[PDB]
Amino acid sequence: RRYDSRTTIFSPEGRLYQVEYAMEAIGHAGTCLGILANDGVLLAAERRNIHKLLDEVFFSEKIYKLNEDMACSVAGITSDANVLTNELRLIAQRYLLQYQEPIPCEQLVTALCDIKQAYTQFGGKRPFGVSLLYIGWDKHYGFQLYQSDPSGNYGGWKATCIGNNSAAAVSMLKQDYKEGEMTLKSALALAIKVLNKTMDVSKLSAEKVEIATLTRENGKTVIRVLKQKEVEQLIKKHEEEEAKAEREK
Amino acid sequence: SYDRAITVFSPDGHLFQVEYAQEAVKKGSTAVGVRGRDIVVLGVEKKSVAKLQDERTVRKICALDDNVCMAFAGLTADARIVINRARVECQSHRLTVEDPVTVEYITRYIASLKQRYTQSNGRRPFGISALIVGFDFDGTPRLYQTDPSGTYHAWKANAIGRGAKSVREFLEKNYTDEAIETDDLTIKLVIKALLEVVQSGGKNIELAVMRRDQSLKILNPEEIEKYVAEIEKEK
Amino acid sequence: FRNQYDNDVTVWSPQGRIHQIEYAMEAVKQGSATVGLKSKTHAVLVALKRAQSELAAHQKKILHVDNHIGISIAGLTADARLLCNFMRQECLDSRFVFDRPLPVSRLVSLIGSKTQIPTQRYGRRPYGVGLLIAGYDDMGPHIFQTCPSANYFDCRAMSIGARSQSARTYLERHMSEFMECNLNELVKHGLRALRETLPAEQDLTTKNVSIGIVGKDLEFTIYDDDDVSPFLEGLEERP
Amino acid sequence: TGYDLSASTFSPDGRVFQVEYAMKAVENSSTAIGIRCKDGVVFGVEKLVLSKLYEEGSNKRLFNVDRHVGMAVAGLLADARSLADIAREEASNFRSNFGYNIPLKHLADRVAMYVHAYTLYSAVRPFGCSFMLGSYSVNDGAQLYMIDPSGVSYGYWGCAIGKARQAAKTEIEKLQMKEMTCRDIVKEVAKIIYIVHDEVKDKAFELELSWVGELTNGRHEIVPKDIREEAEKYAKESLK
Amino acid sequence: SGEARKQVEVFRQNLFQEAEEFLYRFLPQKIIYLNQLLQEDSLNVADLTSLRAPLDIPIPDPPHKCGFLPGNEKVLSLLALVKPEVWTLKEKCILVITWIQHLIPKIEDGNDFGVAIQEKVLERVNAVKTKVEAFQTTISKYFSERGDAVAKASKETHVMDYRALVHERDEAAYGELRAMVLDLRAFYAELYHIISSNLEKIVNPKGEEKPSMY
Amino acid sequence: RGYSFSLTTFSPSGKLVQIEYALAAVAGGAPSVGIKAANGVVLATEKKQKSILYDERSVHKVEPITKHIGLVYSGMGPDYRVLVHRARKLAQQYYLVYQEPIPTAQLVQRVASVMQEYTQSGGVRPFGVSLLICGWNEGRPYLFQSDPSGAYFAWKATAMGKNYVNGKTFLEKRYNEDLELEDAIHTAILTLKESFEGQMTEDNIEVGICNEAGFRRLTPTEVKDYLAA
Amino acid sequence: AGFDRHITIFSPEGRLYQVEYAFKAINQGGLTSVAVRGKDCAVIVTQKKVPDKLLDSSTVTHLFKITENIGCVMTGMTADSRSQVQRARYEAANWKYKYGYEIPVDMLCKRIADISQVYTQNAEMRPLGCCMILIGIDEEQGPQVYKCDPAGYYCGFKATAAGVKQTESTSFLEKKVKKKFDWTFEQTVETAITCLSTVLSIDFKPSEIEVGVVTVENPKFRILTEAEIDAHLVALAER
Amino acid sequence: MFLTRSEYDRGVNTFSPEGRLFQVEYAIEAIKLGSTAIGIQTSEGVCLAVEKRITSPLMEPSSIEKIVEIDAHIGCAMSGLIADAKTLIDKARVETQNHWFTYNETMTVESVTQAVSNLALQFGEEDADPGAMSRPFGVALLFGGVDEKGPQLFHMDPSGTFVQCDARAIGSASEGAQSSLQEVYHKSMTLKEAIKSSLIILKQVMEEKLNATNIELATVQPGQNFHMFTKEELEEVIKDI
């Protein structure tokens, strides 16, 4: 009958349904996209919230700076995300206190993923319902993009989208992304193109998207959230570029 | 009825939740181990590149310590916890007894951790089965396998994971003292066996060899290409 | 239906009865019978041991808590082993602290308190061993029985176990004679009473009878397979 | 209806049934009566003799909870012995910290609070024992207090617990106990105990009588066998 | 396809307005109309003997097809009043059943309380439908039964029970018509009461969109 | 089905139902409106009382966590007090550690974290109250809402409680970013007026204002003046 | 359903049904309590019903003194009521020890009420089914009356009632406050007695009612003696 | 007429109407899932024999270890879940060693069984310690050793009860093997006869034909310590059959 409650019961067929159910939640969440380019890595998210009476007081609703050299975007239950982001920031600071060097990017991801696996194994707690993309530069492997799942399983992706219409985005990215040729400028353009297709709104509001880029300048990583004017220019450039291709057609 | 709790025993004395966790291992990617006279070879299938996904992050074969290497089939996350815990023990034994861990000690430790999870409700059995390959102080090659239940057994050759039944049949027929005679021959046997279950060719197999004192070496994709070619040509 | 109200020790039934405690009481009936009787100078426990197979040895039904106290178990052996250890430690404690053999009655009160806690709290099952405790203390020979329910009773004589009504019946009719009986007579009366419990085909043998005797001058002693022969030989034949 | 399964639950109409079910347990037990007269409090229990094998003067349902206070219990005996232990511990503590014999009204309250706790939590069942405590102290006077499985505690001039509680109360009611002296009441308690006992349903009973008062110098004590015997005779004669 | 939804939405908007109109006006008006009929003297005849209709079948005695035997006029006039009423209730119920079924929401795991309020109402409407459908069947049976009994009486003039049966069948129908109008009056009333009390959940089962947790 | 009862169980479809049910409790709560003007933030809520017998001075829906932060709630009343007390305490802990008044954003993150904690364990029930937190920090007005889920959002203006959806629409139509508080307090009383369902009176409504001076509750006389408009 | 049966689970419409069920328990007792606040006095009156002649009348009371100057009347399950009174008395003393001044009545209701919310939010315990009304004099704000219900609500009222006839009682009191004449001590007591009597239709005798008063002139809570109650009752009948 | 409701079976700590504590009973059934093991105690010594049940030729036979040494004097043959046996064999090994440390003597076979039994009894949630398995253990151990009283074989069951047995068979074919054992066992038999008899019984019960690889046999004669017949020795005895 029901082998899908409690998170600790393997179903006949060996499937942990409560984790699978959690993964379903990420699908409802606003699309977040990350692209890795030789110069820098970028995270762009769709701010699903669009109610007219909301204020942009924070640096970003869905992009969070875990440490000087890394950043993350969250898709899923927001409350669960706040807990994980607090933990990630502590895990990183602990590495710096102990080894006096910045946390290598994979390690921060591996450690959070371990907290996520535990919640699945022990009986009382619900599996965390968040999937998050981490972008960072580490001396060992340079620029890296990693995606995490409620399962606690993490992967390194050159480009990926988590959230609503994620599949469409990955398909578009699969044809569009050129390996070894991406530059932040081109990538920001790829992001606008994929985001436009995935988002239902015909015109990206430029207030409906948040794009943040991590680049190493002068030996120090800079994570900058592009300001609205910068994004508006990108949307206009895309609108014109696509229109020109239609005009040629 | 008797399948909802690990502690409950079925009329007929079967603990169902432990058996179900073993089913999970079957869904996982195949892994094969052959104990050659001087080399132990561990080979695992790779599901797919996915094109936009970096392959460095996904590694089924890992080194628990200098003399012990482990490959896993089952829920990936659980493996990362077990592998990490085994690594702490390997180093802790070295601290406590000053001596490198024998392959069996690591197998017993990994097994006990799993049994501990099966014993009490409120924890789910780790859904991983592992092949631990190592060379002992005497230098005898040793291959051991562990299951979510906590039973450890030594196998001259074995396959865990999807298609394990098919490969194990192939191995039973193919394995012989003659096959293990040459270190290359041993690598060829595992590659040939994985080929039986892998939908693709060499592109989808990750293989690694541990020599008598050398550290684990993951063979480069090109070296694998050479081996598959020799096997295909001989076919 | 009424399937409900029987699941846990913490649920009172609509008519004031905690069913699990009653179900636990049924466990004593499953065990082999044991008979305990007392005389002004001695207290005796006799037991009918059962064997898994001819090759297997008969189980131990009589266990020594202390020089002055011994118990016979009827019911789940595990609960008995656990309770016996508690009793033994409580007795050892009294000798270390007060250098006096623990009054037998006080020990039974302690067994009752430990036994009651499982009955009121969710968690541990009620102990399902029924225990007959026999000892000689300064007050005199004492025979007490403990139910899986924590309630305990002081008895002139008692039989707990399967087909124990038959033994209680014999004991009641021949009860007056017991007070002035000699030890041989008292064990003999008891062996006859347990004989009633046995199926008609079965007979008391040296192998299935265990006798434990405690008295003013006798430390609790469990006469076993070859040492029950003196007490058994004098007995007659089945009525 | 799942309302009655636990004491944590409250029925839609506001009733916690598990406590009420526990109260039904006391009715299963044999009757016990306590009467408070000017000199002191006399308690009596009809102790059914289930088997001839059981020793007389054993399986007592009257317990001394402290030198000055005595407890008579009805209901599941195991719980009662355990409650008696809680009471004795509380009495010891009051003497140890406050340095004097516990006032009975306080004792009843402390034991009641312990009994009430079981009512609230779901892990533990309500206790199934209803008990009466009585004490005589020159300063306090003679006090009889009865505690239900609910933890309600009240002081009763005369009280009965057990299967025949309703019948006994009617008899106790016609007693003018306040004027009566302790020695006379012992005969009266016996008469009531004999009247309530049902010979057909219950084969036989041994009356256990205990008393605390000026006569006992404020020590609860089992009534001397001479006094008990005289009373049992008075009772049979009255039964006629 | 959008065009398809538009037409169906039009049907829904019509159903909603008609259903609301029916609850607001037709149901209350009918309860008064049907109660008027019950109060009417025709349905309150004191002596059932007055209802008896003549059966002119020759009674046999020791020494032709019977003259036309007409149906009790009183019963037919009453049936003629009742048969339209039975039909309107069945039609008005069907309009309500369709409206609720249309309003049932997309099946979803949570917030199924509203679905339940609707399902409970559907049970009452289903029960009423069976009872009313039965009433329509009884009207047809009365004519056939009276007819067969009359035929039997003519074939066997001697048996007088057959004569009594015809008179009895008519009296029974009269009692049942009174009950059926009383039931229709009650049914109109019950539907108004269940729908009126539970309208908010019935019209809007899921409720308004909740704040985003995602 | 089974998903509805547990709080640690994700429903097929990944919805934690008990939290959704908890939000439903807030919706049933008395209407509360918050408007963030440039010079201040006005928090107002209906304090309708069943009888004249109740003494209004006894309990206040709008409460001050610190000198510059104040909150209003819609939902279960007992729960508000628990959160308010924890909030007042969390702020004092900030003052002791950093000797500066807590930034409003920081308190809302901290109060929300407490709410999330209640959500995780099976034994506890999610809090059934949503809080509107208003504060003036760094010369800037701030308004935030924390839902039982543990999620905080920042609203220029919002309404929680009965008729929240209609209230928000009225506010979107009547909201101007440049509004001054004196005008804004009027807008809020109008928003509450939409769903009051009774004659508003000074007692029936409770209003609070946050500005450079800090959170204060308008006393009944002041509101009577504003209501006179 | 199943939405009821655990305090923690919330109904699909967010109603926490178990807490509501508890308020029903207060009524099951069958007793009503009325409290009215005067210009200088606060009075609590409750119906005293003694079920049996045997019960000592002195022991049965619903009026308890939390501290010398705060008095409470608790309606609901008797056992739960006593439990809350102890917590209140402990809390009242703990305030004096920690803060050095007598707990203000409002703060005692707040603490007691807050304890009730914990029960309402934690799974194992059951909301205590009792309502406590506290009467006290605060020097700054004059007389005070506060009620805490099983939910954790703690409002303070000019006048209030708890029990079977609370709604009717509230209506009577509401009419009397609306025609405000202010209340002298006599009137405050008279209003209370008339209200309880009218709602119950009892025509009370001194024994059936327990009345407790706090006054600015004598701040200590006192439970009036039967004679004092009779005097007020006689006056009500006379006029 | 079938009443198959059950409903008291699930959950230890529940007594069935009739007081049967079914979960423990079900655990006793589990040992039947295990390979048969037979022990004969003779004056010359106690012999223990088990069927390996090797699933695949690739699995190394030595690893399957159904007969193990608790200490030189006492050895154990286990049938049932292998994993829970490993815990019980470990408690035994530590307890024998703890006795040497504290009392400088060798524990009798009975005390060692009592010691492992005490651990088995704890399944009832008897203790408050977190690290105790809630489920009754699913293994049955036959413990045989030469002690002060000479060769002794004790059998332990998931309930935790232990008894001396002159000969016992635990396992899938225990019923039937026991019957055969009853006919063959005579107190006077020498170990040589017993080894042959036990292997004859195993050959009959085992599905596969007996081969040195499929069986494990051990003996603890009074002078010698626990000895496991090596393949060569096993080959000689099997040939005699």
Image: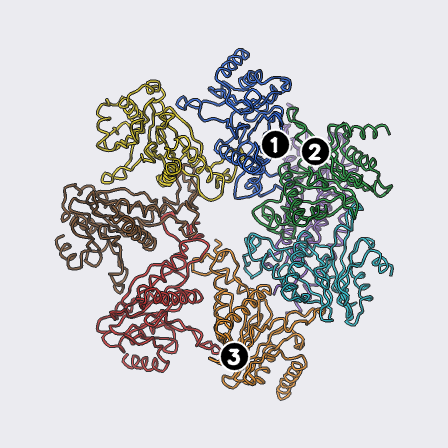
Chain colours: A orange, B red, C yellow, D blue, E purple, F cyan, G green, H brown
Residue farthest toward the bottom in the current orientation of the protein: A248
User: Which residue is under mark 1?
Assistant: D105
The quadrant of the rendering that contains the C terminus of chain E is: bottom right
Q: Quadrant of residue H212?
A: bottom left
Question: On the picture, is H51 further left or further right than E73?
Answer: left
Q: Chain of mark 2?
A: E
Q: Secondary structure at mark 3?
A: strand
The quadrant of the rendering that contains the N terminus of chain E is: bottom right
User: Which residue is under mark 3?
Assistant: A137
Q: Quadrant of residue D188?
A: top right
- Which dot marks residue C61? none
Question: On the picture, is D165 further left or further right than G69?
Answer: left
Which mark's residue is nearer the viewer, 3 or 1? Answer: 1
Q: Amino acid at mark 3?
A: Trp
User: Which residue is under mark 2?
Assistant: E171
Q: Is residue D32 visible?
A: yes
Q: Nearer the viewer, residue C161 or E30?
A: C161
Question: On the picture, is C79 further left or further right than H241?
Answer: right
Q: CA distance from mark 3 to mark 2?
A: 97 Å
Which mark's residue is nearer the viewer, 1 or 2? Answer: 1
